[PDB]
Image (cartoon, rainbow, N blue to C red; front, side, top):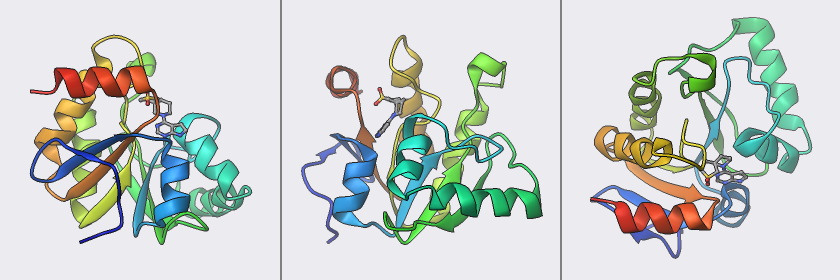
Length: 167
Ligand SMILES: O=S1(=O)CC[C@@]2(CCCN(c3ncnc4[nH]ccc34)C2)C1
């Protein structure tokens, strides 16, 4: 038994809720929150900018030190850093950027990072809101992640669409 509340069950191990991941993190304080990162750990908008803002920029300060030491992540890769005031740990995961021409198959590699953690609070990666992109993003999550993942979907029309379309 864990502390996540109000989630719909998609499969044995995947749960979903129309929620803002930042509000979910503050309320639950999970062991792992996933950030939808870029390779530079530049947290400007979306999940990353909102998580970072909620840490009062401490996530960005830690991230810049990480990059200065280690260089950029790989697309499809990840690193574990502090969760600051939001979680014990933040797993920064880089999904492919299709508007950069980055291979859509890297999305499966990105989700494979989740399997190194028993339970995670996470957003959809390389999904966005419009088109078939988000549907297929959740399809890859379900078919790749084997650990217990609690998905917070910010857009309610998208949440409703995902639940109603999920096979
Ligand atoms: O939900 S979406 O339509 C699926 C793709 C999307 C892109 C923007 C950032 N998103 C978030 N997801 C969950 N919590 C969030 N808090 C702040 C942003 C955010 C994910 C929106």
